[PDB]
Image 1: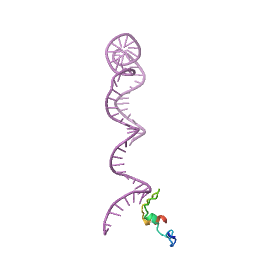
Image 2: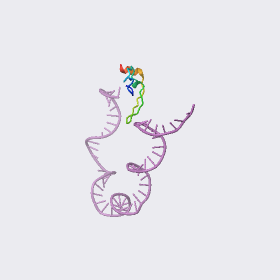
Image 3: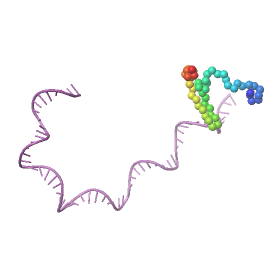
Image 4: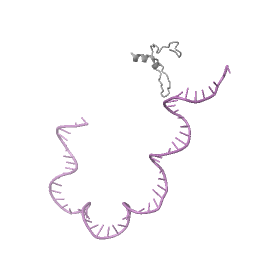
Length: 49
DNA sequence: GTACCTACGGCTTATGATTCTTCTCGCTTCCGGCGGCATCGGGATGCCCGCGTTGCAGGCCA
């Protein structure tokens, strides 16, 4: 549900590509932080296979 | 239409403070350095013969 309980939001997306490993992100929490380099799609598919 | 502040977190870059390490001085005293004498073990020479050295040829090695 949305902020006022009037709409619906999908929890996760039915994706086919691991965008976390392909592009990544760089965010910082209140006490934590993360940083992930991008990668190549073909080698990720090869590793998954 | 046209810019100006910090919060949340991680790696660097610039500068001062601190302790570790090393450079340098301190005169003195004790360990050593040095001159002299009696001494005690040593070198060279006399001599001989037997072992060390060497010439020649044979078989073996790199």
